Length: 214
Image (tube, rainbow, N blue to C red; front, side, top):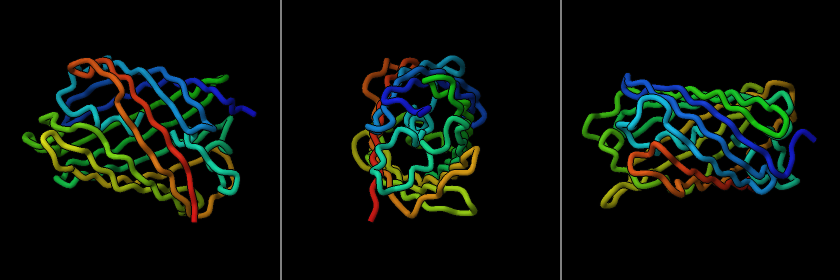
């Protein structure tokens, strides 16, 4: 179709955390039917980032999820026109991040235009003190609402020395053309920073995701 077994990714994120602006660009490769992707990221403005890089990673495409034949795939169906999403990410200590991605397709390459904005992270919290280790794997629940698709997930960052820091995600996905709507289902995720330099100016990021249903 327009979807190939191997696809490319280019992105720019512009954003701010607690008022301090920054920007990151990346290029990657994904396998839409395997639900696997990897990318290399570089901080272009705002670096060395004074907050935990982890809060950014899930913002850097549910196209890269392995869907079985018996579940409607809202995301792959939405191309070549594509789709966009919006997300609120509510951390338990009152830090709040909002992000959007508008995804287009050019040849075999998805292009992301990304906005990230976080506020009210406590100065001595794990995010501003950079005390996070990784996100735990998760299960996103997806359900139709107002003719578009929502996906929510209970997320947790493992912390330095032990313990977890919780964040609730609420995402709304919006196809840019009319597509078949899915029944309620799930997407299991595991995102991981595979390598990074000391201050995360360079990051290699992976995710693998698989849909399942009742």
